[PDB]
Image (cartoon, rainbow, N blue to C red):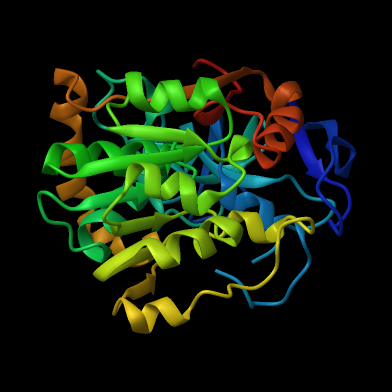
Length: 339
């Protein structure tokens, strides 16, 4: 059987490019290696997730590991089990978890796979609102931000799958919610589709302080931080006393053209702010509680979701670079196969 793959050809130094990846056609006989405790899966959907930017660069165990040069890109996806060496997984099971950028993957361990039971929702949702990004938004907002009705909330990269959901959880709690994004289309989505109280295009603002003051004349209780860089420095002087910064991502910091260093940390003292990082990995004990909350809200239309749908593994490199460059609109999915 042909097995198309997206190979990382070269460890990345500059801003990633399409040619750092190589489309190739391997072969497979769709047989799990002897003694495998893992699964052999047909990949259906693949996520482009901002965090993947950081895995393009060669390091030792010093971030939250790098990709392997000469091997497929790996990331979260949705797949169908063909063969299993783990008796808890069966042929025909739909799963989500870390898989290869290929038509067929051996996933050597199953400990970090979820069996999808609710299929009355698009399967692609388990790469976004019902997968790692949705869980990240739930953990960061409820477990880190200590939110209260009436608090003011600012979300950077607000049109991404994390930010989309943070903002909606904040609106449902009765917070005042503003987002930043990089185009008018994304600003309009945030206001119209996701019910944010306000939003602005940071690429068009000559002074981020003045922009934040337009929307938060008495400051920000909660900053859900996905970007870092100049937005973090602009936010810090606008925090309220006992404000909180949930540090989810600092994506701008992989851009060599982004200002390096945060200069406004004195506001942590002045405004007695808690600035706290977290990893979703530490919160998957909450995943079943999270599904209990989010699945009925999706079916009822109380929560909504925007994905950027890319057709076929051949379009995956361009989609992934587009995400890195901010050229996508909402959560980037790749349709490898519909079934």
